[PDB]
Amino acid sequence: GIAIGIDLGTTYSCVGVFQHGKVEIIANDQGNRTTPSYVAFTDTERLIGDAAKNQVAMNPQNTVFDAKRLIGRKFNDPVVQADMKLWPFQVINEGGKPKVLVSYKGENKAFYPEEISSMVLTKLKETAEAFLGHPVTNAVITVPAYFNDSQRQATKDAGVIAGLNVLRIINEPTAAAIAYGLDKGERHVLIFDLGGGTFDVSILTIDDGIFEVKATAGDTHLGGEDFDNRLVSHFVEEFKRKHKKDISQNKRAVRRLRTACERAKRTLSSSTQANLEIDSLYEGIDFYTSITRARFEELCADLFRGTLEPVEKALRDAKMDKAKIHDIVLVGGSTRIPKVQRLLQDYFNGRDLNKSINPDEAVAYGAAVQAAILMG
Ligand SMILES: Nc1ncnc2c1ncn2[C@@H]1O[C@H](COP(=O)(O)OP(=O)(O)O)[C@@H](O)[C@H]1O
Ligand SMILES: [Mn+2]
């Protein structure tokens, strides 16, 4: 009677199981507790997760990501049409629906967004099966609070394609609240979720175990990727200065620099400096340099400070003052950035923020708790 909880994320996904009184977040084969929502196709194999993201600079047309931006939408949806312009892979109109078109084992192959997502789900499921030592056929899968019926259905369909019985589709902010036991009078909770691609602020009221979404706010195109890109621009300028060379138009160079920037960014959450070392970045030139946390914070200052406007807006929409919020929960990997935590804490006049659960694991953690409840 064992079910898993799955955060099927725009940029990173995560799988947990509640067993013998506690949640285990299941690490992938590289030891990472979260997995990139990436699928890549080569002349010989299909790569999912870390191995797919790792080779993105060498196989841009056939490395698919951001399927969550397509899932449950029609090809003619203006959101899809806008997003298509930003991706290196092809999206085609098949019977009114978007399909990503790739080259795989020497043939053209097209996949629905829910098929791409099913591949990510299948990998997560299989990792859980290896961990537990038996099949897993039940799961709770999470979605953004703003998802419509079509998007929820397509996500549930991804689960069925992956061989799961989907016990429930639950909202991400609700899962995060469940992770912290906030459902166990009225309790008002604010979820601040700054991820890899999206920023969501949710206000929930919880009364006798029942959740009501009181307000949602945010930006569907603000996240960690934007911070990586501020670092990229910075280092593009440093390369123009040290070498009189604009690497800006070499797509591979920019991609490899972005990968290095993401790694450096992560390091800056626990250290005040980070080294970048890119062998042969551009014309056999090694690029060895460094970046301080404080410089990184400056480079992103407008974006970090801008996260407080959706907090204000959500509060206004929920007709609540700051002070009336019982609990604030940090979700999303970008909330590990010290400056983001300071900004939010200062906004809330110094109070404690719920962050003891790794913020990039909290959604899966809550999903895992709820999956076990549903099986009981
Ligand atoms: N220690 C860290 N410091 C800063 N950013 C991080 C850290 N760990 C992960 N990230 C970033 O978190 C983002 C992913 O957030 P996550 O919540 O895991 O996924 P999603 O938003 O797709 O659900 C990525 O931009 C990643 O680089
Ligand atoms: Mn997320």
Image (cartoon, rainbow, N blue to C red):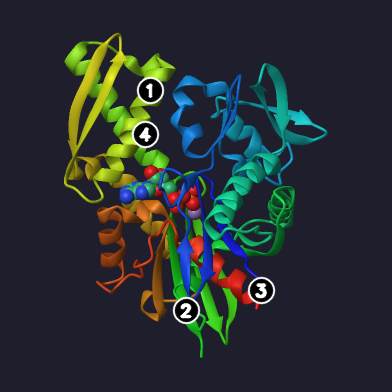
Q: Tell me: residue 175, above or below residue 44.
A: below
Image location of residue 45, percent across then percent down: 60, 27
Q: Residues within 10 Å of mark 2 (few under 14, many from 20)?
A: some
Judging depth in this view, the residue of 347 and 62 nearest the camera is: 62
Q: Residue 235 vs residue 367: left or right?
A: left
* Quarter of the image where the C terminus is located: bottom right
Residue at image mark 3: 375
C-beta proximity under 8 Å, tags 2 and 4: no
In the image, farthest residue toward the top: 283
Q: CA distance from mark 2 to mark 3?
A: 20 Å
Q: Can you tell me whether the CB of the residue at mark 3 lies under 8 Å from the nearest atom of ligand 2?
A: no
Query: Callout 4: helix, strand or loop?
Result: helix
User: Nearer the N terminus, badge 3 or badge 1?
Assistant: 1
User: Nearer the N terminus, badge 2 or badge 4?
Assistant: 2
Residue at image mark 4: 229
Which residue is pictured at 65% across the width and 23% down the height? 104
Judging depth in this view, the residue of 90 and 234 nearest the camera is: 90
Q: Which marked residue is nearer to the observer: mark 3 or mark 1?
A: 3
C-beta proximity under 8 Å, tags 3 and 4: no
Image location of residue 31, percent across then percent down: 40, 48
Residue 249 seen in the figure: yes
User: Nearer the N terminus, badge 3 or badge 4?
Assistant: 4
Identify the amino acid type marked 1: Val
Q: Tell me: residue 19, above or below residue 153.
A: below
User: Nearer the N terminus, badge 1 or badge 4?
Assistant: 4
Image location of residue 52, percent across then percent down: 51, 33
C-beta proximity under 8 Å, tags 1 and 2: no
Identify the amino acid type marked 4: Asn
Judging depth in this view, the residue of 195 and 297 nearest the camera is: 195
